[PDB]
Amino acid sequence: AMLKNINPTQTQAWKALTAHFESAQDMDLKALFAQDSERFAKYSARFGQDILVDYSKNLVNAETMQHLFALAKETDLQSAITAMFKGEAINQTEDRAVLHTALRNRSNSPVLVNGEDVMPAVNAVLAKMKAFSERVIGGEWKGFTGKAITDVVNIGIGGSDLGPYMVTEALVPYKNHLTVHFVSNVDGTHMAETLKNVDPETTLFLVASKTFTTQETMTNAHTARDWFLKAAGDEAHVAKHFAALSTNGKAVAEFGIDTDNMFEFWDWVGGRYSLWSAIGLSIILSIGYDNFVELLAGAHEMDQHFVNTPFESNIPVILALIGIWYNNFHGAESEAILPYDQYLHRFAAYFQQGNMESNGKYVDRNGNPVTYQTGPIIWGEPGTNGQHAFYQLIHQGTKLIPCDFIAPAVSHNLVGDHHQKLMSNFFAQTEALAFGKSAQAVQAELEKAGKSAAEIAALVPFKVFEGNRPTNSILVKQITPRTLGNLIAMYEHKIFVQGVIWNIFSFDQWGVELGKQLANQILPELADSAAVTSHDSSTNGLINAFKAFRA
Amino acid sequence: AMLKNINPTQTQAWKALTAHFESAQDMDLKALFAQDSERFAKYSARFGQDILVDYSKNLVNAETMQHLFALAKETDLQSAITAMFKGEAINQTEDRAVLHTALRNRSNSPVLVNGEDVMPAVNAVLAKMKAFSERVIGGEWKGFTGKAITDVVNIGIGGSDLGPYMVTEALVPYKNHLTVHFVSNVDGTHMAETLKNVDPETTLFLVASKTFTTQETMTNAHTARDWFLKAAGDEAHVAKHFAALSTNGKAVAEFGIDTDNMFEFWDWVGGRYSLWSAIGLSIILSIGYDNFVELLAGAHEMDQHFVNTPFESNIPVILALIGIWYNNFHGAESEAILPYDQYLHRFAAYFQQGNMESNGKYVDRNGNPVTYQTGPIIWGEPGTNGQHAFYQLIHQGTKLIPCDFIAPAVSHNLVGDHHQKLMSNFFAQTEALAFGKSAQAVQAELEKAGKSAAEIAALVPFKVFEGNRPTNSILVKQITPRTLGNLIAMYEHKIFVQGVIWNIFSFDQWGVELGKQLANQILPELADSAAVTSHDSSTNGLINAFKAFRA
Ligand SMILES: [Ca+2]
Ligand SMILES: [Ca+2]
Ligand SMILES: [Ca+2]
Ligand SMILES: [Ca+2]
Ligand SMILES: [Ca+2]
Ligand SMILES: [Ca+2]
Ligand SMILES: [Cl-]
Ligand SMILES: [Cl-]
Ligand SMILES: [Cl-]
Ligand SMILES: [Cl-]
Ligand SMILES: [Cl-]
Ligand SMILES: [Cl-]
Ligand SMILES: [Cl-]
Ligand SMILES: [Cl-]
Ligand SMILES: [Cl-]
Ligand SMILES: [Cl-]
Ligand SMILES: [Cl-]
Ligand SMILES: [Cl-]
Ligand SMILES: [Cl-]
Ligand SMILES: [Cl-]
Ligand code: NA
């Protein structure tokens, strides 16, 4: 196998990083910038014509980077990259390839799985979605009473919801006349509130589930089907109002969906890497196939960069390594993603799944428990909203929180001076985080302002910003389908690199099984009002209190 | 002063906790439950008739609790509680009282500030809001073309946005015919997209800013004013479509608002504790005054519980102490808030400000840098959404993440068996997190599935759940204005308790100043195309790249 299973803690590079942390953990950004006028130039990378990734405000120096790149080499990262792209079954616990990259392979170079090219199958679904979307968007596809579709409701959980919702939100300027809705929670509120806003005669539902047996999704789908049939009566009409993003043709046909409107995907498409497949049909319906292709093309450009660039100028590798420095040496548990863009309000939430479900693992590729930290907690809110909520803690708390600040230079909304104001904050916050403001500086200001020694003693300590809060700044010309594709793929590959180095399996998710099993056991126990005694005292107590509250 | 400044780390209780952690670190939840069938009964509390707080699935035993309550007593928490409620100026760095509790003091017992009872003024603003809301909601208040108002747009940042948005979202079942919208980001997209959805003749804007000079809010307000006037023409009409939540009468009048429609609040109301004041006018407009009074009453109920209950049965104290155990002894950096309720989708975000802006501090009350951890990072998404995104990492990652699971027994929407399915997950997830699943159990399941010995040996470790992931479960009868008030106040007090014990100032926010200062310096530099060289190389580089991109 090209994918190796090297324990990172046993490498010379890791030992060098441990020594370096001991002797340089107090590295100070003000000093790093003061001592090298070319720091920004040396710690930044350009991607294409429209993206700048500035990683200069990180607690790294030439030595740190040298040891980090050495770690990537010593864990045979290049061999792993090759293995993924060529179709090797690197998802070993499920014995599957990992080929979200094939989904956006615009070059159409063959991608073999068991000696057969998967591109014709990929392209056949894409072509089918393009054709279908034109009929729906253009009005030729009629509902059961002869009307054009006005609303699309995507029904799905996790990977079948987060990506499409995030992308359609991020790309609102590119939307067409259709109103798209995303229902995901099994909580009845979600579907109930959506159904109040749509009409059975003009709504198309997409049921997004590979197995077509996902409990939450099928519960929602059946609720929608019931609602639809109250208006339509004849199940034959379901075929004009429901499509499936699935491979279970028998179940799909039984539901009443015409299998011509079943859009397939494959085992090598992980849910959390699936927006690029048939799962992206809601994106195609919202912004059109031209824009969806731009999104795929942007991901493809980043895929090409990731495969072809030496590590020292490879953006996903650099970001992954800097992240490892904080996670495994500085002991930071989290990473904040802070887009200064309201349309990107769901971007951080998307990476909670993409990152945390991939790398939230504790058993290495050899089947041994890890003795080091794996994936971090991802969180964030768009600026300036998050800025006015929780930045107090980032600036003056007791936790190290690496932050990725992301912003476009050009807004889609050319209203007054809002964008210059927004951007002034984008630039100022990272400057503030890095360099702070010292006690000597604050005291000198209070003295010049006529303050007494007593006032100075009482207030200076609270006004000091220690700084050394590291950040990456990613500046994009404009958030377009292509640049969004660039960004999503960039983080996908960052996640991949970290999982390779940490010697874990990034593409399985065995950690979701126990909760599902236990819920299946509890469900029938909630139907009646009888006392439950079959679990531990807490579960019993909670279930019995629930029954008493209900009746 | 009644608020003391006791360093927690030198207390006998903290030293006892340190000694206890030597053995208590490897506590096991399965074992704790097996050792006492009364565990749920002993580690749970009922609040009124409608709330159960179950803290039994925590890594604590009787000794842990004894030492934790000893810590609360040794830091003189009881005195701090009295100090806050009586109006002592506990916000010492700004020399202010902290009296959000007076805003919901339904009992009207006097609360003195500068030797005068503040309750008549609190009640007068409430009465003014009641009267105004009746005119707006009932249709008597007419727009400039004589039509009743149909939409309300709240403009504010931080505390002037997060609470009202969260509460109106949580209480959608109680809404009247008005459509409410919340604009906060200075990013022009936020206001632009909102304005596309409303009509100048039927929209009322609330400009929420105490100073009426907040850059983001006033930029937004002026954009809205310009849009309104493009349709209305005469500035005199502004008075029928704009109101202010502020104390700056001169600026409010200058904007064109009738000061009869300026609703005031006081310096002792912190922004992140302000939804209970005039800042809550959008809540009153969305759900009516009577429901807002229920919200206040629920907070008041919880306030009474907090002040009158011995620590051993005091919910906010118990939650605070368990949080300290994880933050300061187990070293967990974060806390997840996971409401199994789609309406509560903004609840965790609200507490990002309430918690993190309060306790993300590093200097103690005596002006000395802390040598221990203070506030944690708060994050989360509602179940089952979050459940299908990031629980993989909670179950099988390498980070300890205490979780607060919250759910109502009764949904506001009657939708088939959705609620039983939702609740089956709520109960099952905490059961799974606490007790896990052993290798023996996994091996048995794989053997029954017909796996070969080699297949089993290869897969078993990846399917094991170590458990010992602690949670609190808060089960409420139903999320109503009253129970929501109970919950918000509960967490407010938890935050207060933690800040008292950590010897920090929870009610100031000096950490917001540097970013503002630096943004003020950068803003004028973004107006022209000239190269910027006035900062460090990264800030200069980013600004210059920005200028090149917009050219
Ligand atoms: Ca060295
Ligand atoms: Ca740590
Ligand atoms: Ca002991
Ligand atoms: Ca909403
Ligand atoms: Ca004027
Ligand atoms: Ca830690
Ligand atoms: Cl390599
Ligand atoms: Cl496969
Ligand atoms: Cl292709
Ligand atoms: Cl397949
Ligand atoms: Cl289109
Ligand atoms: Cl580590
Ligand atoms: Cl038990
Ligand atoms: Cl134990
Ligand atoms: Cl005051
Ligand atoms: Cl007033
Ligand atoms: Cl009402
Ligand atoms: Cl600590
Ligand atoms: Cl039920
Ligand atoms: Cl065998
Ligand atoms: Na298989």
Image: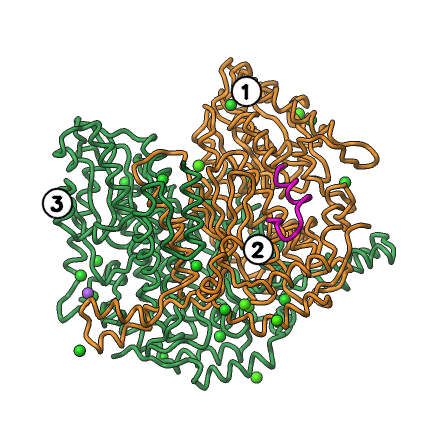
Chain colours: A green, B orange
Magenta span covers which residues?
A: B301-316
Dot 1: chain letter = B
Determine the residue located farthest toward the bottom in the rendered image.
A12
Ligand 10 is within 8 Å of the C-beta of the residue at disc 3: no
Q: Nearer the viewer, residue B527 or A380?
A: A380
Residue placed at 61% from the left, 41% from the top? B302
Is B302 inside the magenta-drawn segment? Answer: yes
Front of the two marks 2 and 3: 3
Q: Nearer the viewer, residue A167 or A535?
A: A535
Residue identified by numbered label 1: B136
Q: How many marks?
A: 3
Front of the two marks 2 and 1: 1
Residue placed at 20% from the left, 36% from the top? A241
Gap in angstroms between the C-alphas marked 2 and 1: 42 Å
Q: Nearer the viewer, residue A525 or A317?
A: A525
Query: Which amino acid, by three-letter code, is at mark 2?
Result: Phe
Query: Which amino acid, by three-letter code, is at mark 1?
Result: Val
Tell me where residue A182 appears, x and y as whole percent. 33, 42
Residue identified by numbered label 2: A427
Dot 2: chain letter = A
Q: Is residue A539 shown above or below A55?
A: above
Badge 3 crowding class, 10 Å Cα cut-off, few under 14, some 14 to 19, many 20 or more, is few
| Left or right, residue B243 beside residue A339 | right
Splitting the image into 4 quarters, where does residue A429 fall? bottom right
Is there any visible trace of residue A40 in the rendered image? no
Query: Which amino acid, by three-letter code, is at mark 3?
Result: Asp
Q: Quadrant of ligand 2?
A: bottom right
